[PDB]
Image (cartoon, coloured by chain):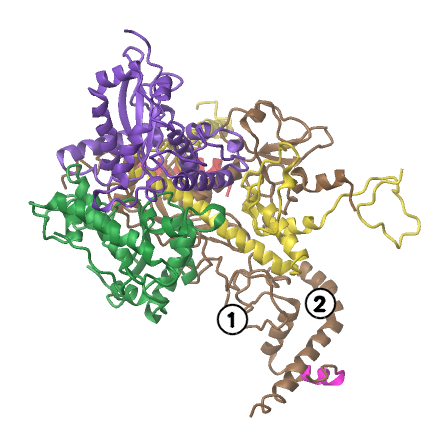
Chain colours: A red, B purple, C yellow, D brown, E green
């Protein structure tokens, strides 16, 4: 199931690059 | 702006001898072509089509779905004038060259008569019946009969609106019905994706309309009446039309290459 | 010289400056144009051609008939000219003349939008097919642009995670 | 009165350009970015167009011709001019497709703009003759003041503490003498209603001290006075004691001039499938997934809240061109801030297949190869 | 052998007051309707479509290139009669019950007048403008406007379907409709009296505007079946 945790890391990474609300 | 232009031989004043009364041609061309041009002006009054020609508006607004209403008025004005422009005040004797290809392609001039007249009535809807000239790069000139619907144009550059087969009485579950349905989506899908089904030559030289027959109700409903009882009607309108065709001009625009 | 005075000069001024300076051109329609286009901001999205053809547009404009004139398109300018005519000839007020010319303008726009939909619907009933529309073309352009951002983000995030982990001086490899 | 040269310039096309309207209002006390700026809520400049024969030459009816590299090649010629001639002796212009094509993409949805509703869904057009009116008479009573949409006075709840003080000092304070007259005209109706109701079995309308006492009587009932004060200053209604007085009146026409349809109560007649149940679906793009726990979708260039219901929950870099979702635009309205807000809803399954069939994307076509 | 049915209130002789003259109704219905039936009888004689009414012939012969001529004449004959079958000799007031639902669907009666008249003048060709009723999620009593373009049947049975009463009751994405009101836009009805419409006078616009003042709303509300909140 740990393979699901790294996905949350990769997801939030891109969310930081979308510098717009 | 687009303005109405006079007719060929003062048809607006006198009209045809035994095909249309001067009052009918007035309501058919003057009081209608002017009505279409008034609406056409309002649509192109402040666009790039303001100074373009009718046929130029036809080819330029053929595929764009946001300009289908502009296509109708532009195509209708072009098709309508194309009809009266090929009528003669007096019957004309069919030339020899044209008299040969018609017999070689359709078998006999009388066979072509019933085919066009038969298609006008068999269509049961306002449209135009064309006499197209198809010549592929390798094949010779061949004449066929194409029937367009309300405002469809025969030119290949405007195949997007070559409205030649109704969808309410041609696409069904029957054997022939399914075939038509497949061709329907094959065109819509090919046109949408940009692919071309029938390769054409540059300049749209494949199809060259030569003759036309306007079957709209505003052209015959008044003169030939409704047609109840077999008298007059849309039938007699197509018959009398066949006598006033300008075969001299039809042969000219055909440009049948001499090979005899 | 003393330039043309498009507006009355300030009478209360006793020592006026800028006497030899050209003055601003203002018409009664400026107040009306600002009112309309502020109530209809998306009317500015309709492209308008300010390029002149022969300068003879005002020869066929008779605003006593309606909003549809010869040579000019149906735009927010037509409402302002029609409003000004009513507000001067028929003696209507700014608000009354505004509502009248404004309502005539809506009924014409509605027919223009209703004709696009119906014109496309009937064309398909007789074997008429069209190309791609803006809704589809607009989305494809976003796809091609979204990918460029994905590559940038994927290549830009590697910079931070690499520079971040390398921030500590763990190069001893104990 | 004007020279023939001045008469031509007046009716000229370049003179008919509308003034630059103020941008869509935002949070006054909130911070923003001044260097960079994205597309605005609604356009503020006029979009310009030319003939194809003139665009190749760079002529746009402006002072100078525009550069060909940045104005030729595209399909839709659209340009926004900020200054016809700036201090750099150049025409500061930009592309106008961000709003020119957003209007065409919106009108492709074929949906009207309805009045804001409260939460029996009743979509009423905004062009109705009873609501869409701006000319009012002095006799206009209060019960019919809620139908209007354009008020002269400000919305007290929307102003900042500073703008409200400036208003009290420069607008309402010097109108005391005028308000006293407004009461006298009412007294003319108070002394005639009781003096002319028995004749079927005008007053002096000029008093000084009677007005002072009538106002005191209203101190016990503050509501009847607010309706009298607001009617004079032309203030938009605030509370029920109805016309969506929550966020305030609209700063523009309720439609904002983006759509002029008055109803969506019509059926789409399909060539093969006859009339349809719902309008054709429209594909949307997913922006800002839940994981704020609210999602945003881009429909026809506008941003709206995702359907009330995955792709909208977690970001997925594997999807090409981002995550996309087929939906149906139920309702469209214009808020008080000028924005266009859409109430998107998820689209059915069969409908998305019918739409994909025409464009040639349906895998299993519903026609021909659909035995069940 | 189908026979010409007589109109409601002798419109063949007196005609409507301000909508159509007795001469126009003659060419519009007395002559045209006969012309269609005569060609229809010649195609159904000696077959299984002799005694069947118009509507049944439409549903039977629909979307097939072999019987296209029958559907056209059959559908046109039905729609034409259905048009004249909703005209009143004089303006009639609209029932309060129908007035309520029209306001719940279109928001106002004026919005309906423009949506129907506007839909007619925007066709550019023949066709019929329908005011059908249907059941939609959220609005048990839904009134919608539909437009058939040429010999188009508004009923759902006249469209393509799938099997597995093998054929489904509704077409893909379609629904069940009840045509209440109709408007004929063929030149046979309006071209004679109103002309083309040059200059803004006459044509479909003037023809459609007058049609709105001669609708038998009493029968429109009847066929609407507003009390049947649920339809199946």
- Relative horizontal placement of residue D174, taking residue B12 as reference (left or right): right
Circle 2/circle 1 CB separation < 8 Å: no
Residue C130 in picture, x, y percent from top left: 36, 33
Asked if the magenta segment contains residue D139, the reply would be no
Q: Main secondary structure of the magenta part?
A: helix
Asked if the magenta segment contains residue D208, the reply would be yes
Q: Is residue B204 above or below residue D179?
A: above
Protein chain holding label 2 = D
Q: Quadrant of the C terminus of chain C?
A: top left
Graded by Cα atoms within 10 Å as few (under 14), some (14 to 19) or many (20 or more), the crowding at tag 1 reads few
Q: Is residue A17 above or below residue C107?
A: above
- Relative horizontal placement of residue D192, taking residue D175 as reference (left or right): left
Q: Is residue B43 visible?
A: yes
Q: Nearer the viewer, residue E68 or A16?
A: E68
Q: Is residue D325 visible?
A: no
Q: Which residue is mark 2?
A: D172
Residue D256 in picture, x, y percent from top left: 53, 51
The residue stretch that appears in magenta: D207-215
Quadrant assignment, res D64: top right
Residue B19 in picture, x, y percent from top left: 34, 35
Residue C75 in picture, x, y percent from top left: 57, 45
Distance Cα–Cα, label 2 vs label 1: 24 Å
Q: Residue at x 68, y 40 (%)?
A: D15
Q: Residue at x 36, y 15 (%)?
A: B255
User: Between disc 2 and disc 1, whose residue precedes?
Assistant: 2
Protein chain holding label 1 = D
Dot 1 falls on a residue whose secondary structure is loop
- Relative horizontal placement of residue D188, taking residue E144 as reference (left or right): right
Q: Which residue is mark 1?
A: D240
Graded by Cα atoms within 10 Å as few (under 14), some (14 to 19) or many (20 or more), the crowding at tag 2 reads few
């Amino acid at each position: 199931v740990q393979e699901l945790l790294q996905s949350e890391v990769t997801s939030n990474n891109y969310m930081r690059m979308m510098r717009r609300r | 702006q687009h303005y109405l232009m006079p007719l060929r031989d003062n048809f607006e004043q006198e009209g045809i001898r035994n095909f249309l009364s001067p009052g009918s041609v007035n309501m058919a061309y003057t009081e209608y072509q002017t009505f279409i041009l008034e609406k056409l002006n309002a649509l192109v009054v402040g666009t790039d089509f303001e100074q373009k020609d009718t046929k130029s508006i036809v080819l330029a607004t053929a595929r764009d779905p946001e300009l289908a209403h502009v296509f109708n008025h532009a195509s209708m004005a072009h098709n309508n004038h194309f009809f009266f422009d090929h009528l003669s005040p007096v019957p004309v004797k069919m030339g020899d060259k044209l008299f040969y290809h018609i017999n070689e392609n359709f078998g006999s001039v009388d066979t072509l008569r019933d085919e066009m007249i038969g298609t006008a009535v068999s269509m049961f809807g306002p449209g135009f019946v064309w006499l197209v000239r198809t010549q592929l790069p390798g094949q010779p000139v061949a004449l066929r009969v194409m029937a367009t619907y309300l405002a469809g144009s025969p030119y290949p550059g405007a195949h997007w609106r070559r409205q030649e087969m109704d969808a309410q009485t041609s696409i069904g579950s029957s054997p022939q019905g399914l075939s038509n349905g497949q061709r329907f989506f094959e065109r819509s899908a090919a046109g949408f994706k940009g692919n071309k089904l029938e390769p054409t030559a540059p300049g749209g030289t494949d199809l060259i309309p030569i003759l036309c027959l306007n079957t709209w109700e505003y052209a015959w409903l008044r003169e030939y009446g409704t047609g109840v009882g077999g008298m007059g009607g849309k039938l007699a309108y197509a018959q009398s039309w066949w006598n006033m065709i300008d075969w001299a001009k039809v042969e000219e625009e055909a440009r049948l290459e001499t090979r005899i | 010289p003393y330039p043309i005075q498009h507006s009355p000069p300030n009478p209360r001024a006793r020592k006026p400056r800028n006497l030899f300076r050209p003055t601003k051109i203002v018409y009664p329609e400026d107040e009306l144009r600002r009112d309309f286009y502020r109530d209809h901001p998306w009317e500015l999205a309709r492209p308008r051609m300010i390029i002149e053809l022969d300068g003879k547009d005002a020869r066929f404009l008779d605003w006593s008939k309606g909003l549809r004139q010869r040579g000019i398109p149906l735009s927010g300018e037509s409402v302002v000219q029609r409003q000004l005519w009513l507000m001067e000839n028929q003696g209507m007020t700014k608000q009354e003349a505004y509502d009248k010319a404004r309502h005539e303008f809506y009924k014409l726009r509605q027919l223009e939008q209703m004709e696009r939909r119906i014109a496309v619907e009937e064309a398909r009933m007789v074997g008429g097919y069209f190309g791609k529309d803006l809704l589809t073309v607009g989305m494809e352009l976003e796809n091609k642009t979204y990918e460029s951002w994905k590559k940038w983000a994927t290549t830009e995030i590697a910079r931070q995670e690499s520079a971040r982990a390398s921030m500590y001086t763990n190069v001893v490899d104990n | 009165g004007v020279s023939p040269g001045g008469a031509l310039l007046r009716t000229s096309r370049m003179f008919s350009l509308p003034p630059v309207i103020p941008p869509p209002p935002g949070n006054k006390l909130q911070m923003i970015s001044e260097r960079a700026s994205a597309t605005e809520a609604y356009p503020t400049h006029q979009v310009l167009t030319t003939f194809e024969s003139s665009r190749s030459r760079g002529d746009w009816g402006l002072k100078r011709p525009l550069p060909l590299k940045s104005t030729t090649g595209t399909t839709y010629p659209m340009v926004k001019v900020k200054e016809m001639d700036s201090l750099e002796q150049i025409t500061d212009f930009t592309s106008g497709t961000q709003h020119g094509l957003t209007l065409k993409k919106f009108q492709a949805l074929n949906i009207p703009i309805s009045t804001p509703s409260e939460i029996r869904p009743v979509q009423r057009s905004v062009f109705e003759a009873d609501t869409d009116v701006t000319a009012f008479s002095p006799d206009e009573q209060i019960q019919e003041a809620e139908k209007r949409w354009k008020f002269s006075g400000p919305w007290l709840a929307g102003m900042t503490p500073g703008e409200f003080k400036e208003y009290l000092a420069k607008t309402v304070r010097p109108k005391r003498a005028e308000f006293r007259k407004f009461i006298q005209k009412k007294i003319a109706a108070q002394k005639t209603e009781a003096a002319n109701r028995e004749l079927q079995e005008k007053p002096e309308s000029i008093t000084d001290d009677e007005v002072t006492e009538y106002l005191r009587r209203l101190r016990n009932d503050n509501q009847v006075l607010y309706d009298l004060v607001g009617q004079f200053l032309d203030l938009a209604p605030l509370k029920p004691p109805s016309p969506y007085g929550g966020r305030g009146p609209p700063i523009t026409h309720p439609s904002a001039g983006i759509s002029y349809l008055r109803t969506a109560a019509y059926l789409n007649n399909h060539p093969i499938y006859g009339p349809q149940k719902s309008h054709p679906p429209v594909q949307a793009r997913v922006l800002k997934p839940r994981r704020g726990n609210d999602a945003k979708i881009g429909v026809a260039g506008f941003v709206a809240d995702g359907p009330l219901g995955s792709v909208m929950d977690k970001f997925d870099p594997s999807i090409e061109g981002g995550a996309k979702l087929w939906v149906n635009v139920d309702k469209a309205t214009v808020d008080s801030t000028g924005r266009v807000q859409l109430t998107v809803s998820d689209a059915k399954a069969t409908d998305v297949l019918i739409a994909k069939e025409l464009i040639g994307d349906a895998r299993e076509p519903i026609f021909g190869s659909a035995p069940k």
